[PDB]
Image: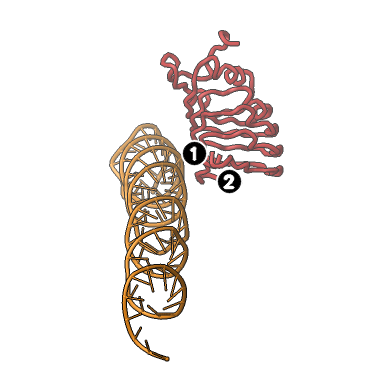
Amino acid sequence: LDFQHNNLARLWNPGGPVNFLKGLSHLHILNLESNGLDEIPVGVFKNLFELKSINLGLNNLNKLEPFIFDDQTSLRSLNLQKNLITSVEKDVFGPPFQNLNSLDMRFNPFDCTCESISWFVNWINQTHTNISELSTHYLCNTPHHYYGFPLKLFDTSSCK
RNA sequence: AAAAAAAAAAAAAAAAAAAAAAAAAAAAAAAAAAAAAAAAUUUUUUUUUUUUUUUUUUUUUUUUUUUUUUUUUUUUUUUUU
């Protein structure tokens, strides 16, 4: 199922969000790139156990609700590049990262802070996921000291 | 049998005045009613024309990366009749 460039942003409060993908078990790859989505409500990826790929790139996503991906235990490739993601939390990207094969979140305003990337930096340090241009297009945007700084070269010894 | 004067009563009819009332018609003044035309405070709805913000489709233009064919400007080491 491919929904590239369809302006689905406001569909996810116009009388309640639409619970799209209701019991769509056999879907393999889902692509919703460049739809301008701003907020993804909880309980929208339920019952998607056999899904393998999610592509939500070229959007503006900064409000990552907890437990968005709960049934995505079989995800193989997650694409979120060229978005407005600021922080990567464990409770949001945990289950999708259990067996992820390729990850793409380049060109994002990452925040090089303890609360934001510590878990992500630890995961990157202790994973074998194939990520392209990890050290080039993953520079942080804030603060000034960490502006334009590689994401992989972050010390988590002062965190947790 | 008839005709007249003082003095006291009673009966029919006509024209009057005052009082107690009762009806019909006509004038106002109050208490209400049903309406066909009116104005004036508040909250909402439809439609037309236009303002602002956000997200995307088509087309056009600028810059950068990469790839394929022609005009080719050159060449170093060689071969060559």
Q: Which dot marks residue A105?
A: none
Question: Is residue B50 or residue B43 the one in the foreground?
Answer: B43
- What colour scheme governs how the chains and residues are painted in the rendered image of this protein? by chain
Element under disc 2? loop
* Chain identifier matching the orange colour in the rendered picture: B
Query: Left or right: B63 with respect to B10?
Result: left
From the viewer's perspective, is residue A63 above or below residue A111? below
| Cα gap from disc 2 to disc 1, whole angstroms | 15 Å
Specify the quadrant of the image occupied by residue A16.
Answer: top right
**What is the chain identity of the residue bearing mark 2?**
A
Query: Left or right: B54 with respect to A93?
Result: left
Specify the quadrant of the image occupied by residue A43.
Answer: top right
User: Do badges 2 and 1 share one subunit?
Assistant: yes
Residue A37, image x, y percentages? 52, 37
* Chain identifier matching the red colour in the rendered picture: A
- The residue wearing badge 1 is A36
Residue A109, image x, y percentages? 47, 25
Query: Which of the marked residues, 2 or 1, is nearer the chain's N terminus?
Result: 2
Specify the quadrant of the image occupied by residue A121.
Answer: top right
Query: Left or right: A77 with respect to A146?
Result: right
Label 2 neighbourhood size at 10 Å, few (<14), some (14-19), many (20+)?
few
CB contact under 8 Å: marks 2 and 1 = no
- The residue wearing badge 2 is A2
Element under disc 1? loop
Query: Left or right: B79 with respect to A27?
Result: left
Residue A122, image x, y percentages? 60, 17
Question: Is residue B35 or residue B77 the one in the foreground?
Answer: B35
Residue at image point 55% right, 16% down: A115
Residue at image point 47% right, 22% down: A139
